[PDB]
Amino acid sequence: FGGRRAVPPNNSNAAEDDLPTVEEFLNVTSVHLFKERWDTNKVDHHTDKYENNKLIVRRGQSFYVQIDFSRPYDPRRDLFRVEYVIGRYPQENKGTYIPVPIVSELQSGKWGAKIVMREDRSVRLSIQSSPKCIVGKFRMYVAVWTPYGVLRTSRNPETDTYILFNPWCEDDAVYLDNEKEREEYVLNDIGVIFYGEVNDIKTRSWSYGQFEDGILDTCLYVMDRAQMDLSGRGNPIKVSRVGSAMVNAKDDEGVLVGSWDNIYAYGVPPSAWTGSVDILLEYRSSENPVRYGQCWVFAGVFNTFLRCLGIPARIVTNYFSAHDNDANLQMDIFLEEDGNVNSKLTKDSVWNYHCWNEAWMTRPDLPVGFGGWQAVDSTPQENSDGMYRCGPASVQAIKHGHVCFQFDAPFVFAEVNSDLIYITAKKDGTHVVENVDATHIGKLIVTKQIGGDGMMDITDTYKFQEGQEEERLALETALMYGAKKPLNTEGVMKSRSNVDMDFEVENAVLGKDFKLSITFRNNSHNRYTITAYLSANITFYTGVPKAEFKKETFDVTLEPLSFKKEAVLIQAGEYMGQLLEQASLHFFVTARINETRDVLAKQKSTVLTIPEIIIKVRGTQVVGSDMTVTVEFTNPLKETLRNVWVHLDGPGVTRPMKKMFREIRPNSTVQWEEVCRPWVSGHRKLIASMSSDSLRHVYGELDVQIQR
Amino acid sequence: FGGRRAVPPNNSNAAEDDLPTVEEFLNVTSVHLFKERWDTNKVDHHTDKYENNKLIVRRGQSFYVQIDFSRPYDPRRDLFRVEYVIGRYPQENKGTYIPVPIVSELQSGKWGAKIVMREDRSVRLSIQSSPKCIVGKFRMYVAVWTPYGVLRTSRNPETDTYILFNPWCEDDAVYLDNEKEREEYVLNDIGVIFYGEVNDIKTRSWSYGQFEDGILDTCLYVMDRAQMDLSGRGNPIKVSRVGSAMVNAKDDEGVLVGSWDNIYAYGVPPSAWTGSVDILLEYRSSENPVRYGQCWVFAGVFNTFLRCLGIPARIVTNYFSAHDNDANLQMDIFLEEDGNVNSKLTKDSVWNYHCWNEAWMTRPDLPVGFGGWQAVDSTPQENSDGMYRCGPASVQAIKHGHVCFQFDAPFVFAEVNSDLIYITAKKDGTHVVENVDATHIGKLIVTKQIGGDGMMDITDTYKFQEGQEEERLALETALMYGAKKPLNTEGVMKSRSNVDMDFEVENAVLGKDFKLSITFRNNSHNRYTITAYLSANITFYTGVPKAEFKKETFDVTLEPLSFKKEAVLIQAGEYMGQLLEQASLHFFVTARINETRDVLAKQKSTVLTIPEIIIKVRGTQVVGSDMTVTVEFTNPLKETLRNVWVHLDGPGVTRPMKKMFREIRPNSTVQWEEVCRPWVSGHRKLIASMSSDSLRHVYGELDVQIQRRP
């Protein structure tokens, strides 16, 4: 029936059919998967770290199982085979129903088994899985082909077996050829998210926690909620392409609700989150989108999803990101007739930093050469389909402008290759392009280094160094495939009468004043008069201004070779009042060389140094033994913070925790003593954060070393 | 009455027409090029080492010049421009006539001279060349505008200016972004060529000598000989493409005439050469192809040509090399039914090693992603054009199998990716495919390291690791574009009943004996019988055999789970009698599994270790001072060597020299002392070679540090 299709879609790893026990000789008393987390199997499969009771193993690699019989296995007349099935509608044709046959010799990526030793009643087999196997939780049944009918085992929940990707197996589409890379990109459950701005790069630890109790199952849960076809779950392109779309909630849909309002009335403010665990568990339990996440939060969660299933993944930060670009390689900045920054239209904003992920895999859907790191960005933005995550887009294709190859490459290409165009919004409704900035746009792309907590400059992966031939070509190539530069930048724009002008912003602290030094370097043998303008705005990290806080203006003169340094002083009581969550200010320093009428423009942004939370541990750093932990946060502002949430986190040390303090008087210090009883050995981190209805985006971490 | 085209073709850099001296009174008195080898132009341009009087500069980078006039330059009403010309038929629109406009600012990308200092009568200019400028020797003039026409300087050879490629300039196609690479790949005039065979890698020094007196000019003559269009000489692609085709003399036209017969009667044996200088110089003087070279020699000479012009280049040795393929990805080995190697037609051999060049350049003719190193092989072979050099083929396209992108890619692809196919030529005229060896060809690809004389493995730039997924798809895309697998290994080869046969081989020196150990190992729980055969040939380094010095047979019995090792001693008496120039030896060890009918084939090659020449310097190692050199050669044979020639070279230390010895008694020792007076200091190197009739391909090198003259 259902003229649509013979058997209904097999899309729930949770739905299960029960295979018939009896459609005759030999019957299995017991099956012995050599589970145990210190045992050969999990260990050799690099799955020993999952807090999981069932056997977890990796596709394309063998494992041992011992089947116990009612009487010696007799190789002459006795015949049996293992079965692996998934979904409510297996179909051997589709990979959901898999019969492992007892064979002589195991060969290249082909399901198979070998009696590796047989004794009184027990055969120890070495079963191998196919490197293209589907990823999920399978059911195992041992069948015996009696001449009358096949009689198989019963539904035994204790034999459920998970099969994950295997970055270690050379035939797996997700194979990382380096061990160091595999520990970092797959095995590490802690990571670092780089934020702030290029000149003042800040960092913060995040608990990926892929091995934490219940994550594996919820990742499977995610795909089910996505009705993801089971035969697709063994393909990296689709897992990631589908997973990435569930991360951000489209009303009731995905995992996290996005929010960039400095309030966060009904959820946990994005800045609060210490890791993924907290979020995924809440999702599963609630079966509803978690309240409030933002760009680096979406990447943190998605990175858990990839590393848990076994796909090599990493979080990347782009400095000065052209998100919401619609494939335009030009961001507009509108100027006033005189030269001041116009604000009627200057709605487009660059992000101080933007976080997206990179997943490792091959691309057999593309020419050979585009495999490796694929950029996937769960933070939606309009693409060909309409406001969705973007990618996988091959980084290597991004780099050379082959934006015609799939998964939204152009929208991820324009994020790191746009030109700033400064235009004059004249009177007669006309516009004139003054100057163009081709270098602000994707200054630094960074990711946590394999070594430890340092940053790693991966900029050259997405782009070539400026002025070199290829760079001009890559850009001109992307333009052939749909990327657009609408404002013809006719010919040249400026010359600056070779008047140079920069300006450093002394990185201050919350509440402190700081100076903003402006600099003109007259390189010519002439005298020029300049009317430079200063516009300082309070902005969200996305670059959306909340209000302009200081708008000074300078007449300055540069005689032939007159290098003249002008200086402003930003006053604490001036910004302190309207500051937003990340404490970033943005400045616009435009200018007009009155002689030639060369508008000069530069902009930068700065973040106010908010200070660390202090975590200190007293006690015995030994697994299974109490350890006391102290989080100490000192209210830096001279104002009282109210309803202060402090969060302690640490994979292997504690389940994420929260506590509240009604208030914290100005300049006061609070203390939180919490005992943790670890279960993981080695290098671990405690992670902390603080959020109050006033200030937030404060963190702290400590690397403790534990043993047994 | 010249209807083909209006202006004849401008194809010689050596030809010059004369520019009219007339068609106001600011006449130039003289011109000052700051072209002393210590001066700032040659030094800032990295052309300080170049035994050349004239100014040598590089595209896209400014250099200082100074003109003196008869009466002070008045900017308000004086007009003049420096002009640079090439060939007998210059033309502005064809970039062979360059009127340098006196700008007020150096425009990035175009020609323009900026006035730097003006101090009375003299104007000191800062001239800037276009990074896409034609490479060659231009003529310089100063034109002074006059209401009644144009006033121009006379022909002045003193001012002839050379413009070359610029690896240091970012707008240049030839731009290498790492200083140390620019050093190795461009300024280094000494190089090492790797040879022998995969697991006994021999090395020898080769003198590129790109800076020696006269080479630069010889390079320009190579292009004139080819009648290469001047407008095209600023193109690394066209340059290497045209340059490469002149190395192998296709009858009269060309630098070298290759010969591989081991006799080399009427010329110089290819193993005697010490570097390129000797060859290129012999070529211009005679104006005819130089007698005898083989692949590594072709690669050496062409390396000089490249580096000397300014295009980064390096020599690459490929290990088991499938030359002369026809874009075919399979190599035929013909068995008998017994298992013996049939030589009825098993005419295709894999070269022990093959040398080719790599030029660093951009590939604006292909999609972005194909710039970098491009292989160019001046050893002809049949491509779509018909028995020519192959390349430039981009090494990324190759590693990726994107072999549809220009400059003979499938042919270079196949040199490094062939499969060995063992086929049985059944007596009824039928053939069976027994075994297929996918990992023999292109085992290792090496090149001299950036640091010093070491070896660097560049294997993974040509291929992905044999075994992974990306390695398969590459191969399959190669098949989508012209590479072919004639035979179809029809789902079979499999594990030949689980019997691993292998054979290690030691390696002695000429005159010594050695032995082989064939190790058959039964990995199954069964008794097995095997009939093995050993074919032991004497080969030319290109695999071409001259004779089978030994033929064996064994019958073995492999009990369940066991090992077995047949050892065989090669008496130095069989091979010594008929060894070839490079002391190469090849072994085939085939073997049939009686019960399963499974065929096990394995082949390896061996070069015999030859004792080196010893070089000894004595005296003061200083620029200008005399230095005594000693070449000591020990005839490792038991016959009297007749007509022995010893060669000495060392760019910057000596012009290459050769000396003869009518004969040399058994095991004896012969020595030569030649005094040398270096003119270049720092780390130098002497290189020597010996060739006789009976023996050749023996070398020697010595690094020396010449301190400077106070």
Image (cartoon, coloured by chain):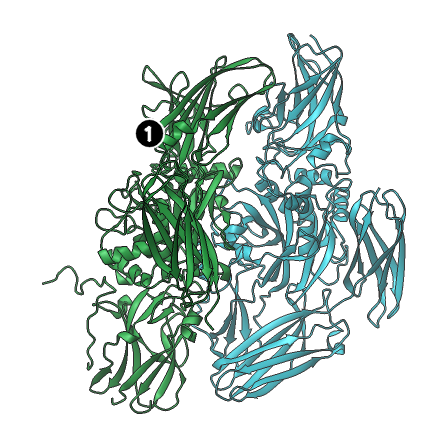
Chain colours: A cyan, B green
Q: Residue at x 86, y 70 (%)?
A: A667
Q: Is residue A55 left or right of residue A96?
A: right
Residue B114's place in the image compared with B121, above or below, is: above
Check disc 1 and give the amino acid type: Lys
Q: Is residue A643 visible?
A: yes
Give the tally of numbered discs.
Answer: 1
Q: Position of residue B69 (x, y in %)?
A: 30, 87
Q: Position of residue A244 (x, y in %)?
A: 63, 46
Q: Position of residue B664 (x, y in %)?
A: 35, 43
Sort mark 1 into few (<14), some (14-19) or many (20+) by Cα contacts within 10 Å: some
Q: Is A468 or B568 nearer to us in this picture?
A: B568
Q: Is residue A222 left or right of residue B663?
A: right
User: Disc 1 designates what residue?
Assistant: B347
Q: Is residue B459 left or right of residue A91?
A: left
Residue A49's place in the image compared with B3, above or below, is: above
Q: Is residue B305 visible?
A: no
Q: Is A530 or A114 nearer to us in this picture?
A: A114
Q: Residue at x 84, y 53 (%)?
A: A658
The N terminus of chain B: image quadrant:
bottom left
Chain hosting mark 1: B
Residue A515's place in the image compared with A614, above or below, is: below
Q: Is B10 or B389 nearer to us in this picture?
A: B389
- Check the image and name the residue furthest to the left: B1
Q: Position of residue B150 (x, y in %)?
A: 23, 82
Q: Is B684 or A702 nearer to us in this picture?
A: B684
